[PDB]
Length: 263
Ligand SMILES: O=C(O)CCCCC(=O)O
Ligand SMILES: [Mg+2]
Ligand SMILES: [Mg+2]
Image (cartoon, rainbow, N blue to C red; front, side, top):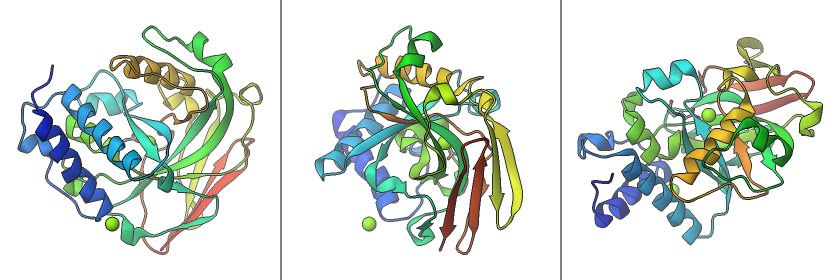
């Protein structure tokens, strides 16, 4: 189920990573490799992860993307995708994000979890996930595809680490039993006014179902979710462009707010 040579996997990972590291867009890689498969793209993504680990970056988490019924159908896929989170992606509550290091960023409000027991697929279900959740973390993702004008496809997007670039944590980081992730209301304000809202159910019907799905996806490569993993479960709100000068505040029902400023 692969079409790339090893040399191509290595060179594509360099090419795609350089676009993020040097803040420029690129053509979608499937233009040059039309036969590229999901396994190829994940090969490329995991190689970019290796490149970052090799230079000393810690991988502090994983994210899930295309977690909407609408999102999957737009992309012609039947399942979500995942990507990894490097330590320098992390931004503190109330922090300042430098847009000069971003290409064409947008923000999404999400809910994250940190696990306290390993999770394995295949066949991981909602019931398997519950006790493995330590606590939840209100999180705003900054997504920033390295493909120009968002002219892409899901295979290219996987290869580009699912557009990951920054994430901002904040609010109250509470045990799972204190929080209903299905009914969790989230309100995104930008420049002083409400611009988007949503509920946790927008994530596959339940954000914990996204965690179960992630375990199953990882199992396809013989991987799993180790205890202690931070997982961003998916977009609760629609993605919103951000630019220098913007202030955002995202309010999480019963869990405070997450804020950031852009320059
Ligand atoms: O849902 C995500 O977090 C990944 C989205 C990747 C595609 C995009 O850049 O819009
Ligand atoms: Mg650089
Ligand atoms: Mg996201």
